[PDB]
Image 1: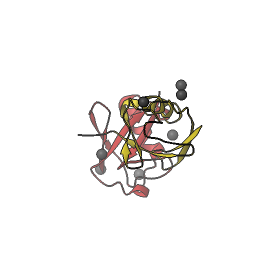
Image 2 (image 1 turned 90 degrees about the vertical axis):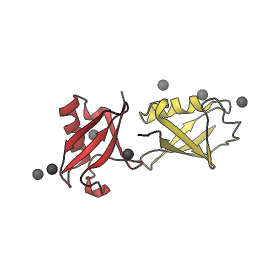
Image 3 (image 1 turned 30 degrees about the vertical axis):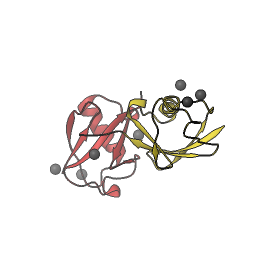
Length: 73
Length: 75
Ligand SMILES: [Zn+2]
Ligand SMILES: [Zn+2]
Ligand SMILES: [Zn+2]
Ligand SMILES: [Zn+2]
Ligand SMILES: [Zn+2]
Ligand SMILES: [Zn+2]
Ligand SMILES: [Zn+2]
C-alpha cells in the first residue's frame, strides 16, 4: 500500500509500505529516498508523534494516508 | 520556576523558566528538548493560544502549569 509524507516546505513524497511496518522501518525508507538519517526525523500522524517500534496499523494508518515529517538537527 | 509541557508524544516535559520569559523563549526551550523549530510550534494554555511576543506573566501562568503543545501545519 501507499502512504504520503509531507515535509515542511510542502514537498509531498510517496512511500511503499506494509500495514505492520514499524516506524523505525519508515524512517529507513525516508533515508533511502531523501538521505536523511532516521535519528534526525520525527514523524507525526493526525496530531500524534509516532514512536519507532510501533506499527503503522498500531496507529490505524491505512492506504493513501498522510504522515508529516519534522526534523531534529 | 517550573512549568509542564504536554508534547506531541503525549508525554510531558519539565521546563525551568523565569516569569519574564516570552513565548518565543519557551518555544526555543522546547526546540532543545524535543527538536521542533519555534516556527512550527503552537502553544495552548487555558483555552488561549500564546503569542510569540507575550510573557508568562501576561497570561499569568504560574508554577507547575501545563501547556499543550501543537503542530503548526496547513495545506
Ligand atoms: Zn502497495
Ligand atoms: Zn513483507
Ligand atoms: Zn529511531
Ligand atoms: Zn496531515
Ligand atoms: Zn529563560
Ligand atoms: Zn539551547
Ligand atoms: Zn509584557
